[PDB]
Amino acid sequence: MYQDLIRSELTEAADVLQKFLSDDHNIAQIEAAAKLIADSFKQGGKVLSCGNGGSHCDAMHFAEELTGRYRENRPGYPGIAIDYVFSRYVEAVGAKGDVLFGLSTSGNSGNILKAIEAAKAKGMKTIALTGKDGGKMAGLADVEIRVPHFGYADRIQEVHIKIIHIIIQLIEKEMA
Amino acid sequence: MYQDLIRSELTEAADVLQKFLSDDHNIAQIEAAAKLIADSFKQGGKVLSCGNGGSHCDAMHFAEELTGRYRENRPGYPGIAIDYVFSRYVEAVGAKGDVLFGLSTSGNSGNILKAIEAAKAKGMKTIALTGKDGGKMAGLADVEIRVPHFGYADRIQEVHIKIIHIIIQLIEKEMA
């Protein structure tokens, strides 16, 4: 049996989650990011979500949940998902007022870093969900939500999913 | 305020997680799941995963997360992600000794229920990560991992992903 080892991963997730919600800053960043997408939507814009390998699944669902909750009477798609692979999609499909939503457990994903630069060069606000110390994109995005974890991606990927879920239902209230 | 709402979702996830890890049965189920798959692996088997939105990504994470860690010197693919769509796939690519990994927050997803039936008919073991009361999936899977929470999907999906991460690491040890 591996009761203790298995529970330890679970208790670690608990510790990580605690450190995250106890800090008012993250709670505020969570609110800022949802306020951005709302405003963009209210001005017709859209959200482009990109996630670095194994994190792109989250980026991909977030876009789906947004399109399946706001397509109703509204042209286009509110949320679309996808080293220059992401930055080429920004230039290609992004417009002023749109938002970039990128996930990177470390703050060092090159394809997402460039994605952020392209958004800036397109009049697009940026939101980055990161881990550790925010890595190289720390401070680069308009709004950064950082998970206080310096170990493997798992605990971080897990908190990103909670953030995404919370952000989505705030947007609904934002839209009201 | 509005942030107190953000914190209430987070602490709600804190509660659900705490409840989940406080039941030794849940922990034993996690071990029985990784054991099943590991055994399958040791006889040339593979895991077929599936879920419906939100759970589609989890099914996707698990499979690709499996291939990366057990592709070395193993023919084929250790893991593959997918009302009769899932069941038709099991019938076509599934084989005796294989494992069906299904996720359904409610436990009543018809396509996954079909998938389970085909799995049995194929001589395949089945694992199901559920929530709420276990739905119809309870008593059907060879191993059920139920998140102790009766409510929307968010809290459950959030624990399902935690389970997946843990299961992946447990396969390394459960078969090393």
Image (cartoon, coloured by chain):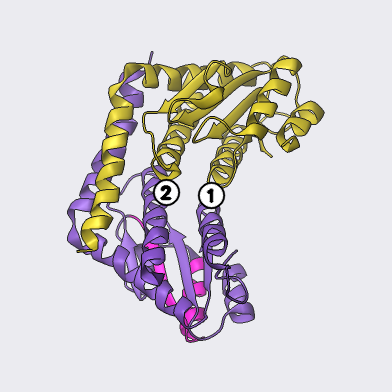
Chain colours: A purple, B yellow
Inspect the image, locate mark 1, and give the three-letter code of the amino acid beneath it.
Gly
Q: Residue at x 44, y 19 (%)?
A: B29
Instruction: Reply above or below: A164 against A39.
Output: above
Region in magenta: A112-131
Is residue A120 in the magenta section?
A: yes
Q: Residue at x 52, y 79 (%)?
A: A45
The picture places residue B21, in percent across and down from the top left corner, at 31, 27
Q: Is residue B96 visible?
A: no
Please tell me the numbered disc located at residue A157: 2
The picture places residue B43, in percent across and down from the top left corner, at 68, 16
Q: Which quarter shows the N terminus of chain A?
A: top left
**Please, which chain is the residue tagged with disc 1 on?**
A
Callout 1–callout 2 Cβ contact below 8 Å: yes
The picture places residue B116, in percent across and down from the top left corner, at 66, 24
Instruction: Reply above or below: A113 against B112.
Output: below
Rounded to the nearest angstrom, the CA distance separating label 1 from label 2 is: 9 Å
Please tell me the numbered disc located at residue B55: none
Left or right: residue B55 versus residue B173 is right
Which of the 4 quarters of the picture holds residue A76?
Answer: bottom right
Is residue B60 in the magenta section?
A: no
Inspect the image, locate mark 2, and give the three-letter code of the amino acid beneath it.
Gln
Q: Residue at x 30, y 66 (%)?
A: A31
Earlier along the polypeptide chain: callout 1 or callout 2?
A: 1
Please tell me the numbered disc located at residue A54: 1
Nearest to the observer: residue B59 or residue A68: A68
Q: Residues within 10 Å of mark 2 (few under 14, many from 20)?
A: many
Q: Which quarter shows the C terminus of chain A?
A: bottom left
